[PDB]
Image (cartoon, rainbow over all chains, first blue to last red):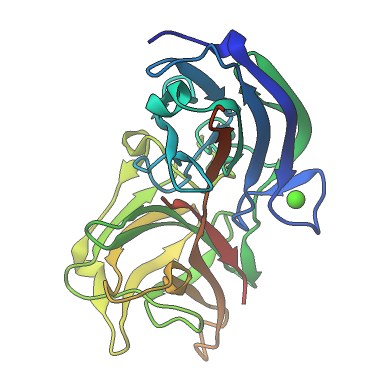
Length: 321
Length: 11
Ligand SMILES: [Ca+2]
C-alpha cells in the first residue's frame, strides 16, 4: 500500500461557515465551525492498502475541546466501508486507507463533509484575518475569514467573561476558563459565584469541583481566545479558604478589593445521564460593591454551553460487469 | 464521532 494522492481527482471543494448571519467572520466564541466539503474520484488503479491525505487549515482543529475523536469512515450506500481515516495533530492531516472495496468496485467517487474549529493556540487574538486553506490529495481551496472573539460583560466595576476549554466525555467533566476583571477596574468587595444551575443546562458543583485561581501581572495580557495553554506563565494564588460552596449547586469565591485581572480554571462534572451535550451549561456571576456605606452592589454574569458538530464520508462504486 | 466547542452568553 502506497500514496495514491496523484490518482485522486478532486471535482469540487468548498469551505463553508457554520452560521449564515456573519459571513466572512468566524464567531469562534459562538462555536461557529468551518465546514470543508470535497468530492473526488478514485482511479481504478487504486488498490487495497493505498492511502490518500486530507488537510485542514493549520489554524484549525477537528475538535476545539477534545483531542480524541473518530475520523468518519467513508461508506457507500449499502454500508460497505471504502476507507478508514486517522488524524495527525502535528500537521493537521488526515490519512485515509482504502479497504478491499477498491479491488472489488470501479468508478469509485466519494464526498467528505468535515467540521473543524479555530485552533485557539494558533489564534490568540481577536480580529485575526486568515487565509484558510484546506486540501484533499493534491488539490486545495482557500477562503479569507476573520476570527472574532467575545467581549466581557460589565456592570459598573463588575466585569468578566468565560469559556469552556475542555470536555472529558469519559469522566463526564468540563473545564471552564474564567477571566475576572479583565478590564482592570477597581472592583471593591469582589465575589465570584460559579453555578451549575443554568437556564438551558447544568453542571454539578460540589466538594469534588476543582478550582484554581491565577493572578495576571501588570505586564501581562490575557489572550482574547479565553484559553490558557501555559498556566505556569501566571502566578498561582489559589487558596481554598476563600472558596465556599453555596446552597444552590454553586460556589462563592471571595476576591476582596482587586484592581488586576484574575483567571479561574474550574473543572466540574456533569450528569452522565444527559443525552444532549448542549444541556451542559455553567454560569458565573461577579459581584462588586459600588457603595461602601450602604453595601449597594452590582452584578455581571456570563455562561457557557457545550456545542458540537459532526463529520461524514460517503462514497459509491460500481460492481463490474 | 463528535467534535466539540462551546458558546458564550451575556445576561
Ligand atoms: Ca460567520
